[PDB]
Each structure stands twice: as structure tokens, then as C-alpha cells.
Amino acid sequence: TAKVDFLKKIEKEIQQKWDTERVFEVNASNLEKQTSKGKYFVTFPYPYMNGRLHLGHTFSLSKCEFAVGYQRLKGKCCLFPFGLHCTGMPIKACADKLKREIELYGCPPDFPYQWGIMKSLGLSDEEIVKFSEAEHWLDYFPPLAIQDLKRMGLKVDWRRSFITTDVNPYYDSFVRWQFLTLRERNKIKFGKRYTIYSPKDGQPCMDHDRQTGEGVGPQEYTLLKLKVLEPYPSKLSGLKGKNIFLVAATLRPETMFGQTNCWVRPDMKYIGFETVNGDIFICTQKAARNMSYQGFTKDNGVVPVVKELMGEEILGASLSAPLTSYKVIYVLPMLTIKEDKGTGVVTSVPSDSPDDIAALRDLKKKQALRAKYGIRDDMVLPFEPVPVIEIPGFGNLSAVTICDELKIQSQNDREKLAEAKEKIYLKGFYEGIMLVDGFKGQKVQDVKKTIQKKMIDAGDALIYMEPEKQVMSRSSDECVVALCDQWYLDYGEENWKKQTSQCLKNLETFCEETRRNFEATLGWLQEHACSRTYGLGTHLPWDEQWLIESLSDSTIYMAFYTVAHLLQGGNLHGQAESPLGIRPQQMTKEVWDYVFFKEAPFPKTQIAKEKLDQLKQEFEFWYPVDLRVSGKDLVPNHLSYYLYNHVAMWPEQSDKWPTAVRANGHLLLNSEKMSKSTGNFLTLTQAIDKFSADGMRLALADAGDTVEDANFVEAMADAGILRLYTWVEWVKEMVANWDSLRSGPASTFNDRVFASELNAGIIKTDQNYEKMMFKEALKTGFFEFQAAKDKYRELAVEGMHRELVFRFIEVQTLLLAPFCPHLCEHIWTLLGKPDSIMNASWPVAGPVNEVLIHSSQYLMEVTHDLRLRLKNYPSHCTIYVAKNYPPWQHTTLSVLRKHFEANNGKLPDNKVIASELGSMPELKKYMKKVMPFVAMIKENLEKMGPRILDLQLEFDEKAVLMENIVYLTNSLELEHIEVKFASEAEDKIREDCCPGKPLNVF
Ligand SMILES: CC(C)C[C@H](N)C(=O)O
Ligand SMILES: CC(C)C[C@H](N)C(=O)O
């Protein structure tokens, strides 16, 4: 267990060496004169300071942190800067729940959590409360973040970090410029528009301030008024005097000629209220409150409630329903009503919505429904479905003529009502044909929008907006609002959308689906609700009631990095003396136009011209964004707005558009999800404490590198630190016993197989590092290097040669330094090599002879082969490697070799087999082991290439064992393992065994 500590000491040792050495401060005036290879720029989606950083952030980043700890050891520059989001509410949210959960209850509260994990963080109770105002959140968290990274030891120029609210006056200048530019280009606009909106927040709550439904929007429905005729039912008494209409939502309004009644759920609570113009509306409150914030009531947002009840009390009185050849229809119960979607009412469209015929039919069957709630001689019976839409497989009575053949007679078939409403679903959007007196033959799709708008002008119908599913901001469930005010951003452009689809067809998607989620969300993304009024953030330049919502003031932010060290040099809040000496007051809109837009004129400035070209040079050298990477949940929203924008201010400049991004899955701790709510979670500061960040870094590079859910498992970060500590002591020990390593040359065989393994490994390792799939590059360069170093200490019984033993620890201590820098710098220094290790390069992959490795992956095959047939039955073993080409085996290879060397990469008949393998007196009683093993050539030949046919088989098998048996006495744990030629075999294994399947009997 001291293993964890030993690392933990030298990690902070080599850190306070690195940091006092200032190793990562990549400047662009001193490292641009050196014409080296080309830059490498790695940017992270800067997390909020709404709380200590978590593994889900560390894995979301480790893909880049390693990347640069490698792409530097290939000679490329490495600007890995790091931002710090403070905009957006989510800070104003957890501590506002702190400010009112400390308000109405004692300090701390009494019950029968939100405060309790600000004290389960540990703070002596007093400190915890200064949190409820936002400004102490932002004086305290950007520290804990940067300390946990200094301690993770990440390759990050310090002087380029910051804060993103108005707190930091400098970035604010950067945000203000962006928007004065983005307003100049008629990319912003003002309007009164529908948006997901937090009642209780006072602003349209859209994307990164939600609990449910990151990618969710308004759904539109038509709403119908349903004149309720007297006799009203019992509870409606007092309101004699006003026009009352039941309100429901259908999405096939072409169908409403098919109205035959009106459905509500007898045991749902219903509300009725008066609009602004003064008539009476009965929906649920989710519906009511939704209408309200949509200007539907007198004062925007208020529900003028007049009475309450449940549908029980409603069933009965006739509803006169517009557009239907049944004007005196009634309200009937439908207990299967989705109790959230819609109004709490639905329509009765029996001829194109099967539930309804099920609904109708049951009321017609049992008198245990036929008088159920006020159901007279007329109620359900003479109502029959309405032929309005014919669909050319089945009938005008479509939704019936389908469930009267799939026989959904019972109304309790809700799975089989998943059957039903999927039937007349959308096919009935085109094949369905309107038949009414006025559209006979018209396509239901080209008249959909007309029949609906005919019903608005007739004052019979209006238009309803509802949450597609549900949201929780952090609290009160949200709503489409007719927001009477919102500055918003125009992602609905025709031009800008197309030039940006092209910014995507350029930018590199690390996979084949990520692009599909960028198409499907771009061809989906309309204009955006980008202005908050309460929370935290920066204020709009010209209308300062408005603050900027998070997901938009965080889009071009990457260029501040390029100049941050000089526009701030370390004070995140932006109050220390900015290194170059710019007054935050002296960064006019056009001196950004200068520093960023290349051709844009040198402005009349009261700062001399030195710093002006120097901050632009920084920019001009560092940009573009090479590779950014974050979780797969900022694919539809933030990374997206991050593509539009980077076009929007350089719509001309092709070069600076982000060129490559990367998204992973979420992370799992021990194969299960990571929500504090579970107990399966670790803040970065503790993963480190427990596992020696190098040890952690390990389990992350093994987290999986794919976009599908990448898992992190505690144990393997433990076994991590162990194979690490056995290494260091081995490397310690193998430099003590220098006097133990062979003189002369490195000439023996075991030597050369390890030595070509070694270089086989360095390149294998190289190929996956180039391709940033860190797990598979882990496997190649660490697991495969241990086993092959073990196994060449295994078979060098005359001593491991030192000049192979040393160039091997060089390469590994290197190969591994991107994964685990301090421990490698320790080793590299341990060797008494001079410079810090980050001043090393990519080691030279020497000359490789893979026919040597062929043998290596042949013995690992049999190593893996006989580990198997020992399960049944067990100590000794003699292994017959068959003697030679039998007169029936040589010949197979011989004749097939003949055809092959004459047929251009395609092989003959599968019954040509029979005529050729059959018609051979050489094959008179052994074709039954040439035809079952003429599939030994069409099964395992792609396995290697043109190998098992080219007769001579470039290595003696008998003897690449008889050498391995020491390691193979291990790895099979037997005692002795001899090998006979199948010359002294039982002849059931001489004249049977295929070289490549060596047979073996205990
Ligand atoms: C730039 C931001 C939208 C990033 C996001 N808030 C995160 O925690 O990763
Ligand atoms: C989906 C529902 C709200 C409306 C649909 N026209 C129906 O069959 O009832």
C-alpha cells in the first residue's frame, strides 16, 4: 500500500520541479522563430465552477492530455490551455437553493440533499453559508480546480486561464466584442418567440440549465374549442353567462371531421379558467400554466382560475364541436389518457385513431359502461366512426379495418394499442385521402396546413405550444412561452446554415456516427434563445437589462487563450497587473477586429503598436483550433454553437474553422453510472488521493477510447500502481547489477526476437498513438512490453544482454511518459539522463524482421492453445509435431499451389473440389481429410495472408519450441514438456497432424 504513496511523493516532487521550472509555458514569440514542424492546439470544454471536478471531466479530457504528452514527443508545439466557465445560472442555482433552504429553516435545516453536501464537503458549518451569494462561489472554486491540475500535472501554460462572467473584465471585453461583431453581421435579431421557458426564472431556460431533456423543444398542436351546450353538468353552476369551450389537442386536424365525441379521463383533476378576451377554458394546469406564459391570458403568464373538478363531473353535457357532421356530440371517458401530454382532453377520431374505436366499442358492449357516467339512449350508440380519410390498403374506416383484423376488441390492450396508433400513423399522412365535400381526392399532406388555418380564421381554432416531454430547470417544470421579448440568435439562416454544414464536412469527426448526430441536429437547429435576465454572466453590450446565457458566451472563447497570458497573465478574475500593460478600458471593439481579424485595420489606439502585433502574432500562430474534445452530450448543443460562431466572424477565413473534434461516452465507475445520488462517484481531488494521479491516469487511458460508454474500474487502477512499482524497482535493480550483464555482442537468438519484438512494439505503439485510441495503444506499449521483457528475461539464461536491456527501458520509459509523466521523469532522471523528460523525442524504431515475430505470435497461439485442452484432463506432456508432407498432404498443397499461382486472387469451384480432390488415386482413402481440410485453406488463410499454402513455412516449429519450454513450463504450470517428431508418436498423430495444429497427448 505504500506503493500509492511513493508515487504520491515524487508526483508532487517532480511537479514542484516542473512548475518552478515552468516547462509548459509555450510562448509564440520565442517558439515561432524556431521553424519546427507545425503547431498542436488542444482545447477543452471548460467546465463550470459549480463544483469540484469529477472523473467524467477527467476522462472527457484525458484523450487530449495524453495526446499532447505524445504530440510533443514528436516535435510538434503544444498549446493545451484551460478555461473556466462561470456564466450560466447553475452556480446561481445550487446556492440559491442554499439561500432559501437556509432562509425558512434554521441554520442548518431540520428534517424530516443541497446544504448537506456543502457541509458533507466538510466545511466547519460557518463558512458554508457565505456561498448563498454567488460571488464567493467564484472566489473559491477556480482555485480548487487549478490546484487539482497542478497536482494531476497537466501540460498547460498557466498564464492563460481566466473567468467568464462579468467578474473578469477582460474576457467580458472579449465577449462584448464578439457580440458587437455578431450584431454587425445581422446574425443576431430581436423577436417575440416560442421558447422553452422557466416560469420561476423569468427567462427562457433552454439547454445547460435543465435537469431533464437536454435536447428538448416545444411541440405544436392544434387546439379546438368545444362549445359546451347547456345543460351544463352539476358543478358548472354559477357561470351562467359566458361562452365556455372544452379545449383539446389533435395533431391530425385533417381528421377532426371525424369527430364523434370528446375524451377525458374520469379520475384526472381538471381546471377551467377565462382567457384574456373572456371565454372559458377547461384543461389541466400543466396545460393552463402553459397557455398563460403564451399571452393567452390577460396579463402574460397568469392563470385566471374559476373552478376545479375531475372528468367524472364532466362526462355528459353535449359538446358542439367544429368541423364535424356530429355537432351534438358528447364527452366520453378514456381511462388510457397520457396524463401529461396534451390538454387533459383528447379528440374522438375513430376513423383514423384506433384507441377510439376500442374506446367506442367497449362503451357499446357492457352496460357496465353504457350508462357509466350519464350515458343515455343517444350517448354512444348512434355515434359511429366517420369516413373522412381513405387509405388504399384498408378503407375509409382505416383505424377500424386494421383493429378489426388484428382484433384489438378488448380496451385493456395497451401494448396492442402501441400496435394501433402506430398503424394509421404517418402512412395515413399521404396514402390517406380526404373525402369531404371540398377536398375529394386531395392529398391529406398538401391540405394539412389549410384545413387547420380555415379553422383559425373561423375563430373556432387557435394554436397550442407544449413541452415535447417535460423539463426541470433545477425546479419548476417548464413551458413553451410566447416570450413577449427575447434577443435571440439566428441559426435558422439559409446561407449561414449551409456555409456551416460545410464547416462540418471539413472538420474531422472521429467516427461515422458523430457526423450523423451533427447532421440530424443541424438540420434541426433553428434560432436560439440566448439572453437571460437573472443568474450570472456577462451583460449584453447595448441592452444591459440582458445577461448572456452560458451556451452562447462560450463559443469563440478559444482565441482568448491565445492572448490570455498577456491580457491577464494568471489572475482569473482579471484584476492583477496585465503583463503587457493594457487597460481593460482600452480594448475597443476594433482593436479586437485588429488582433483577431487579420486584414482589419490598425485602429487609432492609445496603446503603442508593439503589443498590438504581438498579441495578434500569438493568435495568428496558434489558431486554428486543432482538436477539442468533450462528452457526447455537448454534441447537439455546445460543440454545435461552437461551429456556427467560428464561421460567423470568419465567414471568409477557411483556415481558422475548427478542424477536428472528439466525443467519448460517459464514464462508469466499476461498470455502473456515476451520479452522487448513487455512491458511485469520485471527485478528481480524491481519485488522485487514492490512486496517485499517474495511477489514475492509467485507468483512464484504459477507460476505453471509443465513443461508446467507456468504463473506469478501481481495481485495475490498483493493479496499475503495482505493475508500476514492480517496474521502478526492477529498473532500479537492473542498473545495480550492471556487473551482471553480458559483455561482447548482442547476437543470440532470444535476443533478436525480443529486439525485433521491441521495434515491432514501438511502431504498433506508434500507430495507435497517432490515432488517439489510447486503450489499444496502452495494450501495445505496456502489457506487450512487460510480457516480452519478462519472457526475454525468461529465455536469456546466459543473462539478459544489457544493450538490449537498456534501449528497451529507454523506449518504454518513453512510450509510457505520455501516460504517466512524473514516474517516467523519475525513471529518466533515475537513469541519470540530463534534461527533464518532456525534452525528449520519439525513439527510433529500429529495423524489424517480422518473420521473427511470426514465430512469436505462433508460440503465443500454442501457449493459448494448450491452456485449453487441459480443462478436462495432469502434469506431463509430449508433443508430436508431425514429421513431414504426407503423400496425401504435400499433394493437396502441391495441386492447390499450382492453381493458385495461375488464377489472380480468386479460387476454384466448391464442387470443382469434389472433381479434383475426388479424381485422385493419390486420394483414394484420405480425401476425407483433404476436403474437411480444404476448408483449412478457406478459413485460416486470411488469418495471415498467402502463408499456409507457400509450402516451405519459414520457421522450424519443432525448434522454436524446445527453446520456449522454459517460459512454456510457465504459462501452463506443467513441470516438463518434451517434443517428439511424430516419428516415435502413436501414428494416430504421425500421418494426422497438420503443421500449424501440433497435437499433444498426456
Ligand atoms: C463550455 C461549457 C458549455 C462546458 C460545460 N459546462 C462542461 O461542464 O463541460
Ligand atoms: C396524439 C393525440 C393528441 C391526437 C391524435 N389525433 C389522436 O388520435 O387522438
Image: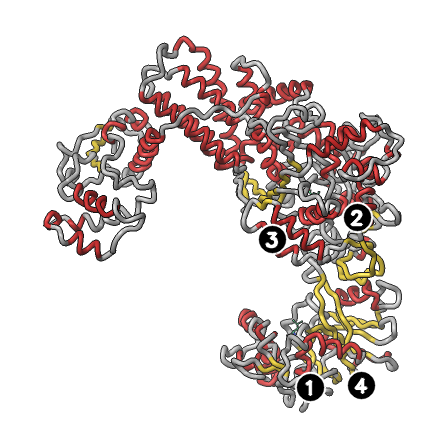
Q: What residue type is labelled 4?
A: Glu
Q: Nearer the viewer, mark 4 or mark 3?
A: 3
Question: In the image, what residue occupies the spot 66% across and 42% down?
Answer: 658
**Sequence-wise first label, 1 or 4:** 4
Q: Which of marks 2 and 3 is in front?
A: 2
Are discs 2 and 3 less than 8 Å apart at CB? no
Where residue 191 sits, quadrant-wise, is: bottom right
Residue annotated with mark 2: 182
- Residue 517 circle label: 3
Number of numbered tags placed on the structure image: 4
| Mark 3 element type | helix
Q: Bin the neighbour count of mark 2 within 10 Å (Cα to Cα): few under 14, some 14-19, many 20 and up.
A: some
| Mark 4 element type | loop
Residue annotated with mark 1: 438
Are discs 1 and 4 less than 8 Å apart at CB? no
| Mark 1 element type | loop
Question: In the image, what residue occupies the spot 56% across and 35% down?
Answer: 700
Task: List x then y, in percent, for residue 900.
Answer: 26, 46
Residue annotated with mark 4: 230
**Sequence-wise first label, 4 or 3:** 4
- Tell me if residue 394 comes above or below residue 182 in the rendering: below
Question: In the image, what residue occupies the spot 56% across and 42% down?
Answer: 668
| Mark 2 element type | helix
**Sequence-wise first label, 2 or 1:** 2
Alpha-carbon span between mark 1 and mark 3: 42 Å
Task: List x then y, in percent, for residue 902.
Answer: 25, 47
**Sequence-wise first label, 2 or 3:** 2
